[PDB]
Image 1 (cartoon, rainbow, N blue to C red):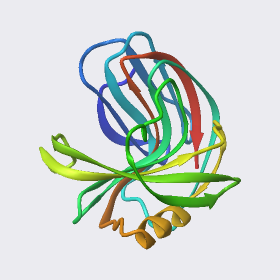
Image 2: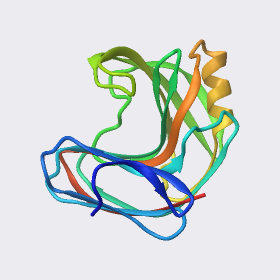
Image 3: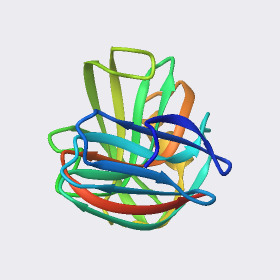
Length: 189
């Protein structure tokens, strides 16, 4: 496993964060590859991509994703000004992260309809410190662990619906887990 933090590996930005509970390892592999193995973890997020992201990136991902419990596989990132945490969720485990959330539309992209949602985090950690901020979600109806994500289709649909993004910060393909178990091996480009 690697030390939690951010950096570059084989031409890709990476971020690996966890809450210190234990039970998760993250490794960077060749090119855009990373692996995550977890067993009765706490909360963590790890993956590879870009710093900064862009608003018209086509992101390719390939591999295996085998959660047992609460986890997501997403294009994940942030903007600043406004501060937004966003997800284009391609697959998940026992919990659909939009459960109970306000639906803000639909968008069709890359072979599936996605449902769009907005949620709010109140006084929570963020890339700029503790803050209250919105999260934007596109949740894929047809789950998969490989594919291509045309981010513009999402960002444009979000904007159409009044979900504005600021200046991009990082943008990765991430495996997130919340007190669960699993394995994943994903290659980004």
